[PDB]
Length: 195
Length: 195
Ligand SMILES: Cc1c2c(c(O)c3c(O)cccc13)C(=O)[C@]1(O)C(=O)C(C(N)=O)=C(O)[C@@H](N(C)C)[C@@H]1C2
Ligand SMILES: Cc1c2c(c(O)c3c(O)cccc13)C(=O)[C@]1(O)C(=O)C(C(N)=O)=C(O)[C@@H](N(C)C)[C@@H]1C2
Ligand SMILES: [Cl-]
Ligand SMILES: [Cl-]
Ligand SMILES: [Cl-]
Ligand SMILES: [Cl-]
Ligand SMILES: [Cl-]
Ligand SMILES: [Cl-]
Ligand SMILES: [Cl-]
Ligand SMILES: [Cl-]
Ligand SMILES: [K+]
Ligand SMILES: [K+]
Ligand SMILES: [K+]
Ligand SMILES: [K+]
Image (cartoon, rainbow over all chains, first blue to last red; front, side):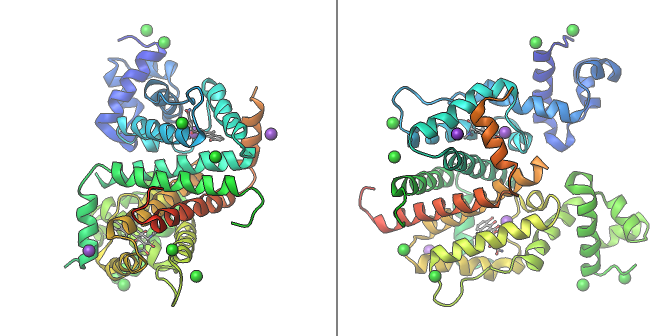
């Protein structure tokens, strides 16, 4: 079938849902695309290349809150950014695993640079803005991965497991996110005060 | 060689460092153990079983801050618990991936029940204590996974990438951890006040 970049990424994302990341293979991708393996090789060299592209494309297609709105607080940007990020990672099977360990792509530079600059414009040093952003990413990644991978007792554990059996992960994520954000705020506002 | 539980888990952990999680196979484990595959099968049924056991054993061997010290604050317990957890996950290649999506084992019940009970004894509802604990786990998991998987530019991104190129992940983890903990504290102390 058609083998332009968009079509290959389309088939690859469809395949990723069928197989998950560890099961996804260029052999299976070729079969999906109605092509022989050496044809596919011309377009996509190996699994790693493909995964790196899927990481970019999942966000490009689905992660829509990548920039603060006009006049938006840094707290509110991080919140919305995290929710958007989480929902994009959840859209494909093992999407958080696809994303892990990737560095911003060239096509993401202006976005990520704006995010970093925005934090500095709200009083964070670059370093502290980065650490806030990284913590949001890491928390959201851990929560998504745990959600996507979870797919006699003592009484509090029994209860806790009932609690987790009770939603998709959203409620715990949102509560934890608020805690994170408020902690950043306590840190920012402290300036050089002991806190 | 010897095929008791401890010896099999020993060889499996050694193998996990050589291969990583996706590359780890029962075929390769048998070879390591000097045995044929059907011998191994008697002891270890499949990769999943093995991984579930490695998740328990990595913590049992290396995660030493599993309980609060006498008189220890809940903030200080979470801090120490997170640092211990992080260091245990980092000890083996793909250790955080091994841990993902596991539920406490029977051999972990008393530990996890104590942790949950401790949070309730410091004023958290079970639910809110659980959410605090889960957020710590998820943040630490995301940070470890990103660290373990990371193994023209606009100027702030260039700087940020220099910043991350600069340590193992520890500094950003520790800074984010403080933020998390302080946010939980702000939430706990608020009681029913709008905050
Ligand atoms: C600033 C930054 C970010 C990311 C990132 O990997 C990263 C890095 O690896 C080194 C230095 C800086 C960054 C993100 O992955 C990313 O997910 C992302 O690319 C991103 C994006 N492209 O919109 C985000 O929304 C951000 N977020 C979830 C907080 C975060 C931003
Ligand atoms: C309370 C709890 C925990 C864990 C967990 O998976 C879990 C769950 O899956 C459902 C309900 C409750 C829990 C942990 O994995 C674990 O890593 C863990 O087993 C654990 C341990 N065994 O010592 C921890 O130290 C805890 N931590 C890193 C905050 C955390 C505790
Ligand atoms: Cl074509
Ligand atoms: Cl195209
Ligand atoms: Cl706002
Ligand atoms: Cl502020
Ligand atoms: Cl034996
Ligand atoms: Cl044994
Ligand atoms: Cl203390
Ligand atoms: Cl307190
Ligand atoms: K990334
Ligand atoms: K700067
Ligand atoms: K677990
Ligand atoms: K209870």
